[PDB]
Image (cartoon, helix red, strand yellow):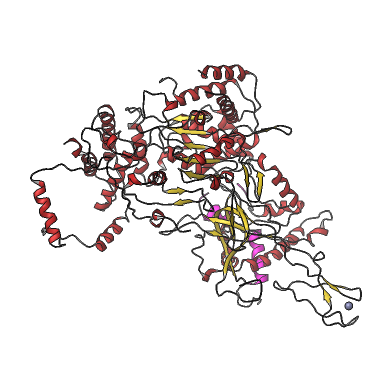
Amino acid sequence: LEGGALVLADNGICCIDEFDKMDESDRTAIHEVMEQQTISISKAGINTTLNARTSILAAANPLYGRYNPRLSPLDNINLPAALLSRFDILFLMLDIPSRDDDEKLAEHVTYVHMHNKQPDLDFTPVEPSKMREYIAYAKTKRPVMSEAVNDYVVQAYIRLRQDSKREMDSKFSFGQATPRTLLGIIRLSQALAKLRLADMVDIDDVEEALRLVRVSKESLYQ
Amino acid sequence: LRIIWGTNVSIQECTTNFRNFLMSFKYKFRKILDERDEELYYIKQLNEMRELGTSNLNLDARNLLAYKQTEDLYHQLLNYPQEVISIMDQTIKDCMVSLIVDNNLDYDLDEIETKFYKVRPYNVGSCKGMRELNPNDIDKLINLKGLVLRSTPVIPDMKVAFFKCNVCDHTMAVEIDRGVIQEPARCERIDCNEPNSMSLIHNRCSFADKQVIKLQETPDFVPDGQTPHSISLCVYDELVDSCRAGDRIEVTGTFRSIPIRANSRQRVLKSLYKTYVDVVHVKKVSDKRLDVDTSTIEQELMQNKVDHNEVEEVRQITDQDLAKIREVAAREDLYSLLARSIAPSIYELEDVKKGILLQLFGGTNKTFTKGGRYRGDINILLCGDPSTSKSQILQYVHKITPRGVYTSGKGSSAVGLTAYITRDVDTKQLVLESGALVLSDGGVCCIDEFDKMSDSTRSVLHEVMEQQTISIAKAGIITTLNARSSILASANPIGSRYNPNLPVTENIDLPPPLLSRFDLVYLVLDKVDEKNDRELAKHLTNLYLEDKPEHISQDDVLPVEFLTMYISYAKEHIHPIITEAAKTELVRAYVGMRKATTRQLESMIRLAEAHAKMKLKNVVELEDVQEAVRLIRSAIKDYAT
Ligand SMILES: [Zn+2]
């Protein structure tokens, strides 16, 4: 047996594009993959519970191409929250013109096309060989979390839960924060501790996690 | 000095060492291996076995690892299992006769001398699937753990090469030499000298019994990019009708090799040798999960009894543990302690867990004289907001249940559910393969994303949910089989983020009857509020606070082992017959709840029978109806709308 694109990926990464155009079969498979790291098949000789252990990274576009500022994301987007709940993170990257930012946006694009060398900042991005060496080394640890951060995480979870449920049931509201949201926050704080290369978690990381979580959708209000 | 060519094994020295270890072993492992009353661990088996006339015996590896004078025997039985066991087959009888010397007995000696003996090393060193078996380590005692897919017929083998001389009214006898027969072409020169006049007859000869089993390997670790495989093996006589489809197995054997012919025409072989495995023992049960229904397997029980092969089929009990069980059943906090114990790593979900445990209890298994059958199984459905422990609970149930399969979404079809026909890769012949619906025959069937699954596939379950009997009519196959499996699956809500102010019987994207016929359903709506969220948050963060949740044992949580043994004994030993008092509450509860079909009556009775089975009651009583109706109404949350 040789598996499909997901199976050839394991303890690694996967990429997908135009998710809205995929079939309900793909939706059913990825739904099971995202939360549980197995796969079930009952077609033929194959009756396996195959191990995926894969990381999913999809992308798509709205129903109308450009955003609908007069409709909520929960309606403009085509995917259902019944599945999107498993998506611990979600960004809404839409564009509105502005006189100043596009100046240097065009500057950057023109420079990179003039020559592949990225802007000549006093900075040297490094080879993916070294990046993979670093990520492999950081993957060796398995840090721990204290109670001083646990209680703050619980308080923030309660805050977000109540605020989103009672207040965010309106124009710019997407569903509600979930236990999966809490688990993702915890996992990302663990990743931050791994990057710092310490076997303990500091209170200085949950702040970053929640900051990014609530900044993912800042543009929805402009 | 006595030794074997190219070997470091001694016959008489090994015999003496084996006898010394046998005479001297008293739970040495409880002392050396760990800190954990009794005496002479081994000797009891041999003392008791004599009167029952059995030519079998089991054997561990940890005992040799523990005793002082068996460490070297360890590697010698490892490298040369067949030779060491052939030595042991004589050493065991030597010890038997040297132990009878201290006893006077009635004249049973006519049997032991003519008898034989064999061993079965079962709990041995671990092996990492088949990837580890590079050709350096061939022909050695090995262990594995996998499930069963396909079983083949009986292969006879020439064991007594009879021969018929054409003249001189004489027969002839000759035996096999390392797996070949050399027919003596001559004709017993003395009486007659015809150098090539003899014949062959099959009815006279003796035959051996062999099987071949296709197995699916289920390791504990796999490399980056692994996928399932299939292996073939060979069992031999006295082990037939032991392992088949629908059983998880931990096994032992001996990796080997063999070439195959290039045709049925001449002797030209392949430079590559097809591998295989020859069995030494099969372990049919384990500690981390209960066992098969006892009434479901009565015919096989009696068949094995008659065949005098008694490999384990059901776990055995101890009187002290039975008394402990009766003591634990005395207290009244069982009804919530079981729920707290099923999943200590999750928030309460009290009624969900209680229903899961009642399903594991199962219920009632009655039959009529010829035209009835009513099995213990109540189909269960889940539904509610995502981002909860529904999938975790389902995976837990699949792990803990012995006989079940996992199916996901629309990746399934009627052909791959019921029986389907395929071809073998070696014999090149039309051979079948069992379907996932039948593989779980007795136990659990898990589904997720029950909504998007294809309508074609959703059609089949109508009859499974009723008579537990699938039917097949396709190429060369006409038979109706049995699928006593149970159903336990999740469902997703219509649209997304749910709709509070709408009838939920129409808020699922699923037709009425398919949902109504479910025996019981559970609802996982959100209802966000403190006093139910901060507690959960700490409950789940303290899981990670430790490297592994062993501090979770606080708050009165039982161990898995005693719980499972209690469940198995209760399942196998008690049969609560329906009572009279429960009628006047059951009928009224059903009628009042109709204000949505008669299947909920069957659901309620089958769940009240499981409740009566709990507490070890041999009789139903009125209270079970109360709990059943109250829990049904709470599960559907009648008070809301
Ligand atoms: Zn003759």
Quarter the C terminus of chain B occupies = top left
Q: Residue at x 26, y 51 (%)?
A: A198
The range drawn in magenta is B9-38
Please provide percent x and percent y for residue A67: 22, 39
Judge whether residue B78 can be spotted in this image: no
Q: Quadrant of residue B364?
A: top right
Residue B607 as seen in the image, left or right of residue B205:
left
**In the image shown, does B5 or B408 lie closer to the viewer?**
B408
Left or right, B489 with respect to B545, comes to: right
In the image, residue A212 above or below residue B152: above
- Asked whether, in this view, residue B66 is left or right of residue A137, the answer is right
Q: To which quarter of the image does residue B422 belong? A: bottom right
Magenta region, mostly helix, strand or loop? helix
Vertical placement of residue B308 versus B318, above or below? below
The quarter of the image holding the N terminus of chain B is: bottom right
Q: Which of B217 and A47 is in front in this view?
A: A47
From the viewer's perspective, is residue B634 above or below residue B95?
above
Residue A214, horizontal then vertical, whole percent: 22, 38
Measuring from the top left, give residue B235's x and y in whole percent. Answer: 65, 59
Q: Where is residue B290 in the image (x, y as percent from the top left)?
A: 57, 42
Residue A209: tell me if it is visible: yes
Q: Quarter of the picture for ligand 1?
A: bottom right
Q: Which residue is drawn at 52% across and 70% down?
A: B135
All told, the count of numbered labels is 0
Magenta-drawn stretch contains B480: no
Asked whether B21 falls inside the magenta stretch, the response is yes
Q: In this rendering, would B496 be left or right of A120? A: right
Nearer the observer, B162 or B78? B162
Q: Which quarter of the figure has residue B611?
A: top right
